[PDB]
Image (cartoon, rainbow, N blue to C red):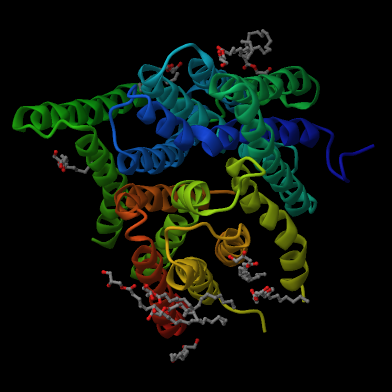
Length: 448
Ligand SMILES: CCCCCC/C=C/CCCCCCCC(=O)OC[C@H](O)CO
Ligand SMILES: CCCCCC/C=C/CCCCCCCC(=O)OC[C@H](O)CO
Ligand SMILES: CCCCCC/C=C\CCCCCCCC(=O)OC[C@@H](O)CO
Ligand SMILES: CCCCCC/C=C\CCCCCCCC(=O)OC[C@@H](O)CO
Ligand SMILES: CCCCCC/C=C\CCCCCCCC(=O)OC[C@H](O)CO
Ligand SMILES: CCCCCC/C=C\CCCCCCCC(=O)OC[C@H](O)CO
Ligand SMILES: CCCCCC/C=C\CCCCCCCC(=O)OC[C@H](O)CO
Ligand SMILES: CCCCCC/C=C\CCCCCCCC(=O)OC[C@H](O)CO
Ligand SMILES: CCCCCC/C=C\CCCCCCCC(=O)OC[C@H](O)CO
Ligand SMILES: CCCCCC/C=C\CCCCCCCC(=O)OC[C@H](O)CO
């Protein structure tokens, strides 16, 4: 007896991530619209450009938090307590939004989910590898199955949560996200005690006695310096919300910038720079689906007969549809890796180029077919299949996605009804050209 040929413990972790992704993307599907609503009632005193910027920097901090969660679990608390307490924080963050509060609850909700996702997301994937020995060949199949559960939750969540918001309002809809995470906790807690190795209730590489102090010193210097920067900012008058967002943008971009300049000072690392740039730029476009495309859907689409948040379901839908195809394709000369990044960046560019057409053809004061966004997501997910689809590279994928959203925090403020065609054309064409450049550089990168 198995779970699709895999250890029974996989079903638990399958369902665990399935409901966490449910809570996350269900929230992402309506959070921007919710901020619009808080703005329209005068409760929240920001612009839509700022609200869009918040969404992007929100995502950036979540991925950045994922780079640290692996460390905390492996060295301090253990992977299983990390997943559990990570989930509790995630749940609380959604409960905060379900409460009878307004804009005041936003920062509290955001902080909880960032810390929570940081603990849970990288360690659930870790616990998946736990299910297998070193020798096991089923590993790639199990992770593929595990990925499928991730996409399932991301698919049904905007459908359920989005419809709930339409029927019973925002507070009820956010509570469904909280309930979704709660279900994941029940299955994880009681299912884990049956199938998970008790060895991972504790850290696998616990701090040696002499390691405690320097780690404590290192963290303290980071917090103090960060606190110091904020102090100076408020002194010189850079203390509006766009200022703090720019600070986090700088921090998010500085982290890979420093690590590169660190390692650079044989030099094949230099050859990874274009790949990392290509990764950042792709994630920038892909992550704008929940921000820019979510805005386009709500303002420019004939979606009068269905919840407009449902458009967020297209991303994991096309992933699930494309996956068995590419699974077959990579088994049936297979193109190199820098080539995949170059072509993947092109498809992302075409997705934005396509969106420039309806505005250029019909104008931007009317409403267009929902099929335009359908074709756009189909293009960028096609590009995803080439670039994105575990170990130590998990950090770089967390980093690349984090930097992209940080870049988005700046870029999405430029998007509006007046700048629609220009926004989609330039960045659309811009990504295609850099995809062409990467093709020219593709041969050198191979062999390094
Ligand atoms: C294989 C599927 C291919 C997917 C097709 C994607 C589109 C490709 C070319 C059109 C993009 C640029 C559209 C032109 C935008 C443009 O003309 O901007 C000025 C405008 O006229 C000002 O009003
Ligand atoms: C399959 C296509 C293969 C790739 C072909 C690439 C096509 C690019 C067309 C857009 C170029 C820009 C033209 C429109 C720019 C535009 O709208 O500018 C407004 C004004 O500058 C606002 O400042
Ligand atoms: C990828 C192959 C299939 C699609 C190829 C893309 C072909 C055309 C896309 C770009 C042009 C679309 C037409 C937009 C309208 C326009 O330009 O307004 C002209 C301006 O003077 C206003 O009066
Ligand atoms: C066998 C699968 C091969 C996969 C190739 C699929 C490629 C593209 C999918 C269909 C895209 C065509 C749509 C463009 C033509 C169009 O919009 O004209 C509008 C017309 O309807 C007016 O009413
Ligand atoms: C939030 C309600 C969801 C249901 C929770 C059950 C109620 C109480 C559990 C005891 C306290 C929690 C202690 C958990 C610490 C922990 O590491 O859990 C790893 C777990 O054994 C892996 O399956
Ligand atoms: C920790 C236990 C597990 C977690 C359980 C999930 C959390 C809350 C569930 C109920 C939410 C009810 C929310 C009530 C909606 C509300 O406040 O009012 C709407 C508004 O008035 C309609 O217009
Ligand atoms: C628990 C969630 C995160 C907690 C924030 C801590 C972050 C930085 C402080 C570093 C030292 C803290 C770790 C405690 C050291 C410790 O547990 O001792 C091990 C060993 O048993 C002694 O040799
Ligand atoms: C890896 C550590 C992080 C990297 C080191 C960072 C060093 C200094 C931070 C830049 C200044 C922060 C202040 C930015 C705020 C800002 O730009 O203000 C505009 C706003 O329009 C004013 O209202
Ligand atoms: C596997 C990747 C597949 C490639 C994806 C890209 C293909 C087509 C783009 C969307 C279709 C154009 C939009 C059609 C709009 C339409 O149906 O016209 C009625 C509406 O009322 C007019 O606005
Ligand atoms: C509307 C008119 C616009 C014209 C559109 C033309 C589209 C593609 C042509 C350039 C392709 C260059 C790609 C190959 C160049 C090259 O040197 O590639 C070596 C590389 O090492 C191989 O992997």
